[PDB]
Length: 258
Length: 258
Image (cartoon, rainbow over all chains, first blue to last red; front, side, top):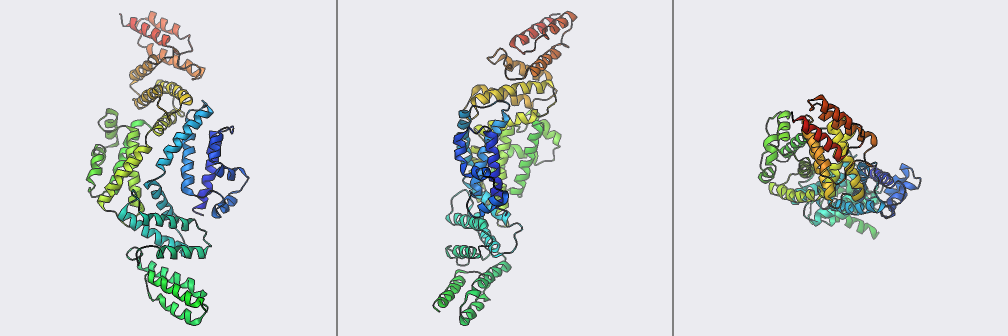
């Protein structure tokens, strides 16, 4: 979708740039650098097929890495195109490629990549339908935005870097993996320092939808009426907390013995 | 798009960024860094007044520098805009600005600036009207394209740096200062090693046009019809050579001796 379509676009664009840079297939060093990507554009796959390969992790699907590696070939294509009709010798092209490589890699790092990754999260949520994944993602992103407002992105912050890791992973995760989504979000809430991490950060209406979501997930998995009675009452809270989640986890433990 | 017109465009875009980042004029250090820009753009000047200031040097008119300085504020605006509705303390904003400034300054340097300047000349020459200025510029850019194909732009080459400097200077030169255009091109041809620096590079069709350009320039300056006929005798050459310009100069010297 919004993410894996850009992955396929970057894969097709890298191959287009490589072919125009090296129209006679002689820049073996550069093509070996990109063969992990180029193979998916040379194997007669359709757009839908590469899309499913990106969702299943069969092809390169790190959009930020693909974007950085596309910029390298784009820079080299600009040079090759701007000196037309004059050809450059093959080893000189590779010499230019190595310098552009380290130059672009430095630019595509530090605060800049974090800034791009935040945009990936907000753009993905721009018109996202209210799903558990999208509710988890919008809650995590709002915490991320609040922490960046307090700490910035030019220095390293472990809590922010964890939100980027888990958030982007949830973003690229398949929409049908309900268990993996619930596991990721419950993992983040437990593995973060604050007790009520969403207080003052999300509207009160959204905080209740989060509580109702976690309740409706474990509700059909109670192998006893008595265990499913108290869990239904835990919806009396309107803020997702670590105590509320541990309360749900304890009910699954008492039901696991039965 | 004319050079100085692009200068005004970036001057305006910098002011709109600053107004969105700091609407109440509290980031004193950032506005101090951009004071040479904002003193023109934060007032109600007409476009033509800023344009005349750029063409006369009264306001910053380095298009690559202005592009670099604009990217810093573009990145800083992205951060402030991407964390909304959460806001950042003013000290943190200026702290993020300093690190973004150093990061962008690394990106907007080295081969990348030269690539932008080469792309700037080739963009301008795309379907450009065959005027003396554009013919002079296309002749120098073609020599620049050839030398780059031979040496690249990732390593420093002094001959290439002079073609950029002279090429961009002629690119920004007013289309009406025709005697200044001729003098620049005449000076490049004389201050370069090759006797005929355009053969093997520029097409023979354009070399003949380049010769006829130098003849149509010095013909009105001829007062006596005897010298006017001596200049047309030089038109039998299809190669612009150092000797052809020395001959046209000697014919122009004896005309002033009357």
